[PDB]
Length: 17
Ligand SMILES: [Cl-]
Ligand SMILES: [Cl-]
Ligand SMILES: [Cl-]
Ligand SMILES: [Tb+3]
Image 1: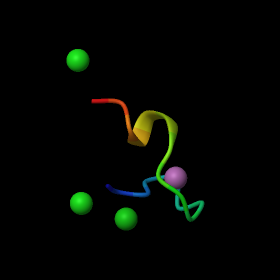
Image 2: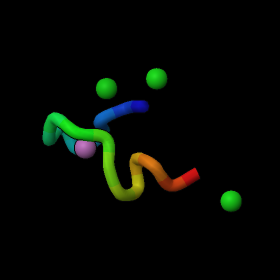
Image 3: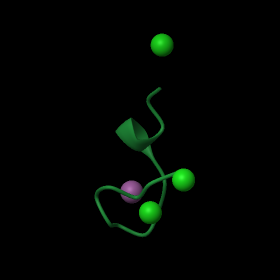
Image 4: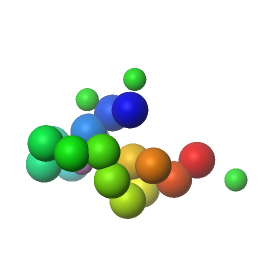
């Protein structure tokens, strides 16, 4: 995964495929 919002987690739209 890519932590695009750099919050330290993989979540939300970062998981939206
Ligand atoms: Cl990756
Ligand atoms: Cl990342
Ligand atoms: Cl889809
Ligand atoms: Tb994130």
